[PDB]
Amino acid sequence: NENRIQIMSTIAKIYRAMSRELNRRLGELNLSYLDFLVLRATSDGPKTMAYLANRYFVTQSAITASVDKLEEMGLVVRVRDREDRRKILIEITEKGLETFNKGIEIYKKLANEVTGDLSEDEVILVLDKISKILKRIEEISQ
Amino acid sequence: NENRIQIMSTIAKIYRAMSRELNRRLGELNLSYLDFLVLRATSDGPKTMAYLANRYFVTQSAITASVDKLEEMGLVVRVRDREDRRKILIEITEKGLETFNKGIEIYKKLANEVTGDLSEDEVILVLDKISKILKRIEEISQ
């Protein structure tokens, strides 16, 4: 078995290809993949820029550029935290949520395509197993 | 099923965590994850910097920095292509190969850890299936 190591490098290969294809397909909505991720995160709740940079493993500059772009398009707004007005949060707008919905459909379509060879039964089995891999490494790295 | 889309986002999450942990663990050998990838690629054969940037989806500057670093440590050397001396290739050195070996063991150990919940039987089943996902998207994106 060079299989375990192969699983991790295959996952890495799929990720790079998926990032590239998603960057391309999301352009239809004038969004980079990172922009999409920022919307996904803020849809979950207001976030600080520091949170976003760490969550997606990108530089602060990447986040600042992404936010300015979503902000410019009225999808997010920077608002001060209520408890301490010195801290700024990135908050999704109703329009941001609407664009997020569209981005998810673009994402769904690509996923349905790339996983097309798998039956719903295999999908569940695969998800369940790679979910174990994620849980293991998330504890380890942080 | 939000499962197919969940498979792709779980793969993305695992990738980010793995990149971070590998960057940490490979530091023991004074290598970033990208440095490791450059060694893996050049181990396969001499490569141009353009090839490396595209293969790993990073900027040319990332590759230049990675190469200078491996070069400085005597793991790779820049050599001119024989057919057209104007083109420069990045070639791994015998020492580079030796360090690559060590990096692979570090990688193997992490993989054995994160996939530990899986039996060799599940490993093969999972690899076979995600290999189908990779083949699908690699054709699509390029």
Image: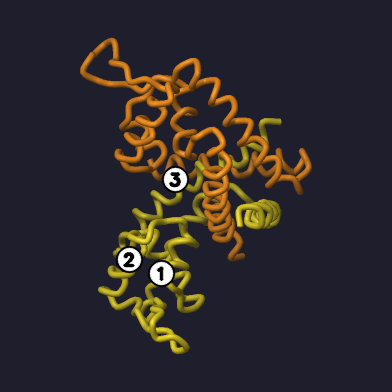
Chain colours: A yellow, B orange
Residue at 50% over, 41% down: A13
- Against B18, residue B84 (above or below) is above
The residue carrying mark 1 is A49
Q: Quadrant of the N terminus of chain B?
A: bottom right
Residue at 54% over, 33% down: B29
Q: Is residue A50 left or right of residue A66?
A: right
Report if the CB atoms under discs 2 and 3 are less than 8 Å apart: no
Inspect the image, locate mark 2, and give the three-letter code of the amino acid beneath it: Thr
Inspect the image, locate mark 3, and give the three-letter code of the amino acid beneath it: Ala
Residue at the top extreme, as displayed: B82
Report if the CB atoms under discs 1 and 3 are less than 8 Å apart: no
Report if the CB atoms under discs 1 and 2 are less than 8 Å apart: yes
- Against B3, residue B54 (above or below) is above
The Cα atoms of the two marked residues, 1 and 2, are separated by 7 Å
Specify the subunit that label 3 lies on: A
The residue carrying mark 2 is A64
Upstream in sequence: badge 2 or badge 3: 3
Res B102 → quadrant: top right
Q: Is residue A120 visible?
A: no
In terms of depth relative to the viewer, which is nearer, B130 or B98?
B98
Categorize mark 1 by other alpha carbons within 10 Å: few (<14), some (14-19), many (20+): many
Q: Which mark is residue A17?
A: 3
Residue at 32% over, 42% down: B59
At which x and y percent is residue A125? Answer: 71, 53
Res B100 → quadrant: top right
Upstream in sequence: badge 1 or badge 2: 1
Q: Quadrant of the C terminus of chain B?
A: top left
Inspect the image, locate mark 1, and give the three-letter code of the amino acid beneath it: Met
In terms of depth relative to the viewer, which is nearer, B101 or B42?
B101
